[PDB]
Image (cartoon, rainbow, N blue to C red):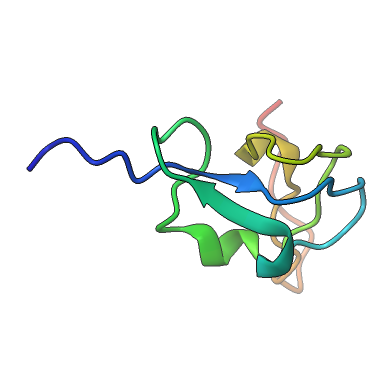
Length: 79
């Protein structure tokens, strides 16, 4: 079927800025894909937040910094 109220990954608790994500601080509010998908959820678990998220709040890609994997200075700002 088309309909899939999979939900979006919302913060399970307040995630203060500068903290790294873990599954113990996340959940997926089954209802609407308003925010981050529960499919790519693992990519979030390891990123750092840019703002103090509140409990049950909708996490977004603009609220997490990019990955710090690549051993090289490249990637111009999209903002």
